[PDB]
Image 1 (cartoon, rainbow, N blue to C red):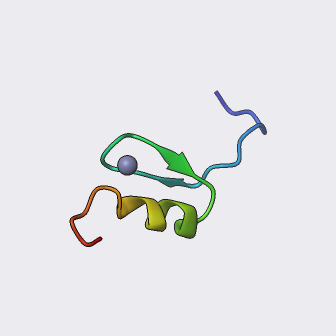
Image 2 (cartoon, rainbow, N blue to C red; image 1 turned 120 degrees about the vertical axis):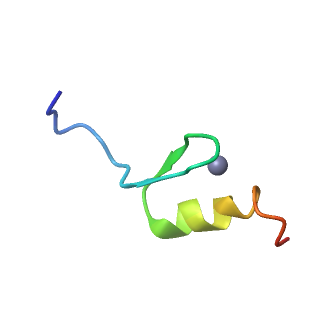
Length: 36
Ligand SMILES: [Zn+2]
């Protein structure tokens, strides 16, 4: 539905997660990519 109760814009394409900013999501993507 269309409700004004949410604070997540970015979403992960590995674990179907969701973050607030590209940072919280970006730093997370690392857990997936073998960049670490
Ligand atoms: Zn993920």
